[PDB]
Amino acid sequence: KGEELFTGVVPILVELDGDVNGHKFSVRGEGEGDATNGKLTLKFICTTGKLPVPWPTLVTTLVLCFARYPDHMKQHDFFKSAMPEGYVQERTISFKDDGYYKTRAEVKFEGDTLVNRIELKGIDFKEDGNILGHKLEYNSNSHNAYITADKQKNGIKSNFKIRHNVEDGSVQLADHYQQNTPIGDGPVLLPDNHYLSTQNALSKDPNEKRDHMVLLEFVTAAGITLGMDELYK
């Protein structure tokens, strides 16, 4: 079924339209995903000029179908099971002592390309806070995010805390509440409780004048006891 679409390297397109305290922006990303290795490589451009929020605060918004699920966990991979029809991914991201993002994305195949199309609205931010004031370091801590099935909506949900490094040495909490539900009507896998382990490397393209982010990301599923029965099938 859907997971057969990810056995090779798959081109990715990301399109985001954002509006944070009335500061509007657009981001376009392109690259490729290698779910066999759990690997994503993308370059993102702010096509509207200057990004009015820090690039790290957008990493989680800017394709969990590229996670590497170990063989003994292939039956808990909701994200690939919804493909190619796709899923809707919705989040509220509450920054502590600051504003919040609300995001709605559609992740689905358009032709041969896996497309992530996002609408983001940000509200109640401090114009001199860590977000609109650009006081966050250009990096992304490694992080584990717990997945649970949402049977009553036929999808998954997850809540997790992102800890952004502030340039003074403090930490800015971004509390994520996330919900995913399939777009099509076909069968989806509802996972047992598990987590995704994520690492992110952020860099710059020397030849790129525009405001941009080069991202390498690894996502690997874990947390389901690989017992001795699975070692004999």
Image (cartoon, rainbow, N blue to C red):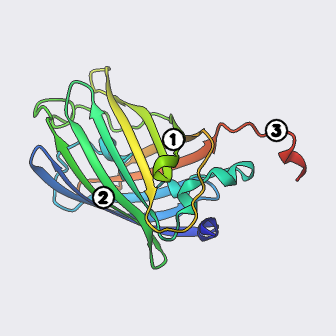
**Along the polypeptide, which appears first: circle 3 or circle 1?**
1
Q: Is residue 104 above or below residue 47?
A: above
* Residue 208 visible to the viewer: yes
What residue type is disc 3 on? Gly
Disc 1 residue crowd, few under 14, some 14–19, many 20+, Cα 10 Å = some
What residue type is disc 2 on? Ile
Disc 3 residue crowd, few under 14, some 14–19, many 20+, Cα 10 Å = few
Q: Position of residue 23 (x, y in %)?
A: 11, 49
Q: Mark 3 points at which residue?
A: 227
Q: Residue furthest right?
A: 232
Closer to viewer: mark 3 or mark 1: 3
Pick whichever, 152 or 229, lies toward us: 152
- The numbered disc on residue 199 is 1
* Residue 34 visible to the viewer: no
Q: Position of residue 223 (x, y in %)?
A: 65, 36
Pick whichever, 85 or 168, lies toward us: 85
Q: Mark 2 points at which residue?
A: 118
> For the residue labelled by badge 3, is the local secondary structure a helix, a strand or a loop?
loop
Q: Do the residues labelled 3 and 1 touch (CB within 8 Å)?
A: no
**Along the polypeptide, which appears first: circle 3 or circle 2?**
2
Q: Where is residue 10 in the image (x, y as percent from the top left)?
A: 53, 69
Q: Is residue 100 left or right of residue 10?
A: left
Q: Do the residues labelled 1 and 2 touch (CB within 8 Å)?
A: no
What residue type is disc 1 on? Gln
Q: Is residue 158 left or right of residue 43?
A: right
Instruction: Kindly identify the residue that appears in the image at 46 percent across and 65 percent down.
Output: 86
Residue 186 figure quarter: bottom right
Q: Is residue 66 above or below residue 141?
A: below
